[PDB]
Each structure stands twice: as C-alpha cells, then as structure tokens.
Length: 138
Ligand SMILES: *[C@@H]1O[C@H](CO)[C@@H](O)[C@H](O)[C@H]1NC(C)=O
Ligand SMILES: *[C@@H]1O[C@H](CO)[C@@H](O)[C@H](O)[C@H]1NC(C)=O
Ligand SMILES: *[C@@H]1O[C@H](CO)[C@@H](O)[C@H](O)[C@H]1NC(C)=O
Ligand SMILES: CCC(CO)(CO)CO
Ligand SMILES: CCC(CO)(CO)CO
Ligand SMILES: CCC(CO)(CO)CO
Ligand SMILES: CCC(CO)(CO)CO
Ligand SMILES: CCC(CO)(CO)CO
Image (tube, rainbow, N blue to C red):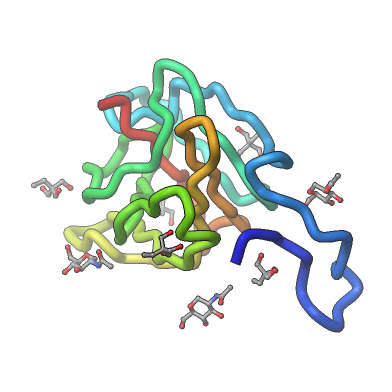
C-alpha cells in the first residue's frame, strides 16, 4: 500500500521506500498545459517517482489536453482522479491525445498523496515520442 519495494523476485528488488520521501523534483514550467511553445521533447527517459513544482503546476491534468502543448506533440493526462492522503499507492491510466483521440496512446502511472499536501507520480518512460506528462497550472 504505502511503500515501493521493487518488483518481487527481480534484480531491481530493493530496500522498500516511501515515495513521498524519495522522488525526483521537477520545476519545468514548459510542462504546463498552457505552454504552446514550438519546441517538442519526450519523457522517454523518466523512471521512478516524480514531484512537480513551479509555475507549470503541481499536478497532472485530469482532463484531456490539446495537442502541441506541454512542450510536446501528444500531451499526456491522468484518466482518473487523484487520491487522498491515506489511500496509498494507486494505479492509474495516463492517456496521450493525438489525431482526434484523447487516448491515442496509454500507459500505467502510479500516484500517491503525501503529507504536506502534494502528490508524487511513478512514471516509467513513454509509449511513444514525442509525448510528455503535462502539469496543470490551475
Ligand atoms: C530511492 O529510489 C531509487 C529509485 O527507485 C532507488 O534506487 C533508491 O534505492 C531509493 N533510495 C532510498 C534511500 O530508498
Ligand atoms: C477516462 O476518460 C474517459 C473519457 O473521458 C471516461 O469516460 C472515463 O470515466 C475515465 N476514467 C477514469 C477512471 O476517470
Ligand atoms: C495496474 O493495473 C493494470 C491493469 O489491471 C495491471 O496490469 C498492473 O499490474 C497494475 N499495476 C500494479 C502495480 O498493480
Ligand atoms: C509495480 C509494483 C510495485 C513495485 O514496482 C510498485 O511500487 C510494488 O512495490
Ligand atoms: C529531468 C527529467 C527529464 C527532462 O526534463 C529527463 O528524464 C524528463 O524527460
Ligand atoms: C474540449 C477540449 C478537448 C478535450 O478536453 C478536445 O477539443 C481538448 O483536448
Ligand atoms: C476509504 C477509507 C480509507 C482507505 O482508503 C481512507 O484512507 C481508510 O484508511
Ligand atoms: C505524436 C507522434 C509524432 C507524430 O508525428 C510526433 O512526435 C511522431 O510519430
């Protein structure tokens, strides 16, 4: 529920940790759903847990984002509702909007609410490029 210990019976199996206390911090305003920049990158290298802060927003969007936002081509949003503190690590689908289809690609993401009023996200690459996990500045 509360801890990430790695995949059982695998080399990556490791000491358990609380994601709320072991994440990569990203302050990348270009992830904003309101960023229209012509540049396009890809989150293909993401791994582990992430916390988003700054002007771009502190959470993923819960609604489909228009294409060519978040400094990417196909933006990714959370096809679910954020958990409350106490719900533990929750399993969700992230959807990428492309070619008239708000879920043209999909992938699993984990989400946990944390003491202090923030969320962390477990993000393992992307299913295609150029895709990125957006943040909603609202
Ligand atoms: C933090 O997470 C990384 C990636 O999952 C892991 O390799 C590392 O052992 C963790 N560190 C601690 C202190 O739990
Ligand atoms: C995912 O999005 C679809 C389309 O907007 C919606 O019908 C469905 O209920 C959503 N799923 C969750 C778990 O929110
Ligand atoms: C999340 O749900 C999918 C679909 O049921 C499943 O394949 C996957 O193993 C789940 N992830 C975890 C960590 O349980
Ligand atoms: C996907 C399972 C698990 C490890 O990868 C998620 O944190 C369980 O600890
Ligand atoms: C540091 C995060 C990142 C670049 O912003 C590289 O993994 C995400 O794509
Ligand atoms: C109504 C807006 C939208 C869905 O949220 C489709 O045009 C944006 O992707
Ligand atoms: C809904 C009950 C409960 C688990 O989700 C709230 O955190 C009880 O611990
Ligand atoms: C959304 C993917 C793509 C479409 O032209 C742009 O990165 C490349 O296949």
